[PDB]
Image: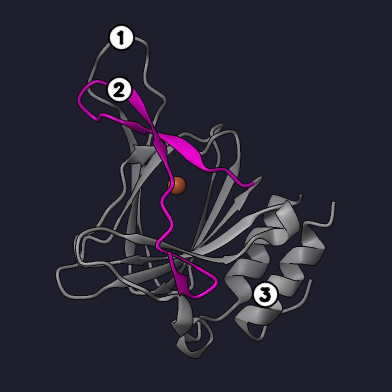
Amino acid sequence: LLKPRTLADLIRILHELFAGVNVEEVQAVLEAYESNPADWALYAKFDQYRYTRNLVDQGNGKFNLMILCWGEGHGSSIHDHTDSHEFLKLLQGNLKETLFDWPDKKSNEMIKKSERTLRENQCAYINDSIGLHRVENVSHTEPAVSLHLYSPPFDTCHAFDQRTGHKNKVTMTFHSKFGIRT
Ligand SMILES: [Fe+3]
């Protein structure tokens, strides 16, 4: 388990780690990579209206690695992770992560577990056993850029209505893949 000097090195180290996964080790190497905008500028493609997903690597099928670009005030739904893992690392700016419990079957306001602000180079980890979350760039002045690793890869998740706990299936949309607009 070595310090990744560049994004390219990080990806190689991740391929080795996923050749079989140890969550703590993945989190450790992600934290250890020091964000360098020169490494990831190609993928940092923004949209005026919502956050974007920019695929970086497909993990020899073991994981999806993508960079998400968040305009001021852009946020996600409250969502799950489709029986998979999500690791997220801040590359620039700040994101607020709000944790929620899984809702009961009754319609009810959703129950907010905790919140934290993630800052540059910090990470977070979530899975369905931990709960649900919402990720948002609450800044009025600064975009955020984050690095997200999903394993196994998945295309869809559920968004939850905070007022009721009811969920709707949604399909991930890609803004770009391998630097190319899609
Ligand atoms: Fe998530």
Q: Which residue lies furthest to the front in this view?
A: 182
Residue at left offset 36%, top offset 67%: 69
Residue at left offset 47%, top offset 82%: 42
The answer to whether 182 appears left or right of 27 in the picture is left
Q: What stretch is highlighted in magenta?
A: 153-182
Where residue 117 sits: x, y (%)?
Answer: 34, 59
Q: Nearer the viewer, residue 43 or 126?
A: 43
Q: Which residue lies furthest to the left in this view?
A: 140
| Marks 1 and 2 in Cβ contact (< 8 Å) | yes
Under circle 1, the secondary element is loop
Residue at left offset 40%, top offset 76%: 44
Please rate how many residues cluster around mark 2, counting C-alpha atoms within 10 Å: few if below 14, some from 14 to 19, many from 20.
many
Q: Does the magenta stretch include residue 132?
A: no
Please rate how many residues cluster around mark 1, counting C-alpha atoms within 10 Å: few if below 14, some from 14 to 19, many from 20.
few
Location of residue 87 by image quarter: bottom right
Look at mark 2 in the image and give the residue it sits on: 165
Dot 2 or dot 3, earlier in sequence: 3
Look at mark 3 in the image and give the residue it sits on: 10
Q: Which amino acid does label 1 sit on?
A: Lys
Location of residue 116 by image quarter: bottom left
Dot 1 or dot 3, earlier in sequence: 3
The answer to whether 111 appears left or right of 57 in the picture is left
Q: Which of 90 and 168 is in front in this view?
A: 168
Q: Distance between the residues labelled 1 and 3?
A: 44 Å
| Marks 2 and 3 in Cβ contact (< 8 Å) | no
Q: Which amino acid does label 3 sit on?
A: Leu
Look at mark 1 in the image and give the residue it sits on: 106
Say which quadrant the N terminus sits in.
Answer: bottom right
